[PDB]
Each structure stands twice: as structure tokens, then as C-alpha cells.
Length: 198
Length: 244
Image (tube, rainbow over all chains, first blue to last red):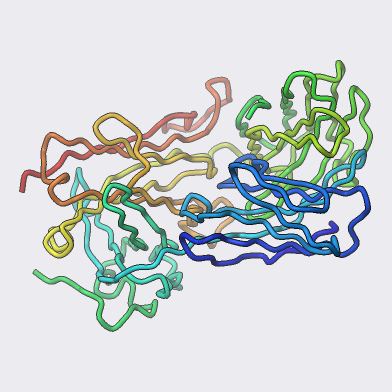
């Protein structure tokens, strides 16, 4: 109600990510609170308080002398930190109200090797899917405007075993027309993309 | 966590009444109710101080009624349910009317209300085996899981390798996507990726399972059609490593 936040925000894995909140009409007796919500799940508390700075295992919170703005600090942003972050203000007795809020996305840096591969179903076996992977994080995968074709949003995985991150989108369809050569051609894939053909 | 809610999910037809329960953390003075829809923040419904409701939002129709008869557990009753009630209903509790004490949230009760229950389908799940092209180019091997075409969309996807849920090497789409988007009753699809080393995949003694928990109808729901009653269940697809 009394808070304003960016709807979404990118931040680099893994330096500190600083989520800003504006609250220019704050009292007095009102504390500032930050919650985080992952998937549809219950929002979990991160940190609060008055007018000041504060810290715990999960994060740090700096509030200006103004009182009129605050900053949440997540000290070493990993992929697990990407979620929605709500900044709320409350001073007692009344209800608590949530806004929007942010939509933090930790982005990893790559040393890239973009390719589009075909994967076959395990049963089956055709039924197949197209995998666009190993692209750098500046590359965006677009939504197919062919309705029968399905393209997913891009997704970052971490092979923690080998200290290796990678991005990937997935495409599939039932059409005859459809193939992997053309699955991700409606996006703007990079010039050096590897397209197998044995 | 440590507040609880019952049930975790509920699918009704239009006419029906529905009742949720929320159990606060022991001796927590305060109990809050919110509702939430996809991509939006929680919307305040009502809150309690001891037994004493307090405030109910001009949201809540008369069809909603929230009780808390012992300043302890709280029930929310929604009468004559409507499509527009479909939402995640969140419970929160707080120790005292005290800014120092934070709200603890429960895991929520995801309500879906329907024109009719013949629109509820479980997922089918297929696991897709890695390309040889990938294996020879990167010496890594990506499996893909596809969950289709289910409704509503409360599914939970998980990869199990050699009998343990894994999180390293895994990616799942934040949201599902609509199969015919296009429609009111659009059925959904979700994909996930598991990436391993080429050599790990090329060992036939390794076993890969894709598990999707679906939250559907109850055993006790009136069911009409030929196909299996789309109850709450887990659908799976398996794959072993290819010696190749």
C-alpha cells in the first residue's frame, strides 16, 4: 500500500543483489519487512525492522535516515535466490497489505556453446523434443506465435558437481512441418548456433 | 514453517460449499487470511486478534465466513462457490500485536472451482533421452521430462536418480504453458531438464525417473466419464542409461 518496488530486476550471480523499496510516507512507528515467495508457495519472511540497519543468516537490511527508502541485501546471489520479494510496512494493530513486488532473477555468466538438439522419447519413440541449450544469458528465447508449437521460457541449471551453469529452452509440436532446424528460428538465436545433422 | 493448513488443495463444482482450516503456531495471538492468484501478491481477506475478528475486506462476499472460536485454529467457509473464487488461500499467524514478531505463513490451500469436473485431467509424463550429438559435442547429456496435458495446474515435478530426489543438474519451467491458449479450460504442459555427464548417462546401471504429483479430485467426488477418475496421484516416466 505504502510501498513501491520494481516489478522485476536482473542481478548477477553471485555478487550481492540489492532490492530497492520506496516508502516516502512511512511513520514513525512502522517497521519495514521483506518477504520472499517461490513458486505459488507460502511467502517466507526474510528480515525487518525500524530505522536503522539489520542482519541475519539470510540477508541484510539498510533503511535510510530519511526513512523514505530501504534496501534488501542478499549477499551472494545464487540461482536458488530467484523469486518474488515483497517489501511491506506495518506498525501494529492494523492489517498487513502486500503489493506486487519484485521478481528477482539471478543471471549466471557463461563461456558459451549454443546448440539445438533433438531428444527422443524413452518408450516409444517419436514423440520427440527440441532442446536449445548452452547459449549465453543475453540470448532470449521467444514464445512461438504458432499455437500448435510450444516453446518454453529459458531455464538455468547448475551442475554443482562440476561448477557449471547452463541455459536451455525446450520446444515441441505435433505438426509434420515442425522440426528442430525451424523450432527456434522464430527467436533470434546467435549466428554460431550448432545444428547437428547426422 | 510452522503454521499448517487443511487441505492443501480442493477442486469443487460451482454449487458446492467448501471449508478450509488453518492451525497457527502455538499461542500466536494473531491470525491472517489472504487469497492469491497467479502472478499477483496476496490480497487481504480478514484477520483476527484473539477470537475477535477485526477487519474483513470489502473483497469477501457474504458467501465467505471466517471463524476462530478459541483464538486458536481458524476456519474459512466459502458457500455456493464461484469460478472467480479459484485461488490460493493463505494463512498467516503472529505471536503478539508486536512489530518485533513476524508473520509466519502456512503452505496455503489451493482452491479451483469448475463449470464441471470432466475438465479435470491428470498429466501424462514422458522422459526424453539425450541426443548423441550433445554427448559427442559437450560430453554432457540432457534428459527432458514433459508433463502434459493436465488440469487444473497443481502439479509438482521431481527427478529421481538411483532412488533419491536430485536438485543438482535440474531445471523446471517456472510456470506451465497452455496447450490451447485459446480456451477457458485450456489444459497445461510443463517441461523439466536433468543434465548429467556423458559417461554417467552411458552406464546402464543408472536409473532416471520423472515424477509428477497431481492434485485432482477426491475418491469421494461424483464421477461420471469412462476414463479413470482423475484423482490426486503421481504419474511417472523412467529411463535407464544407454550402454551405447
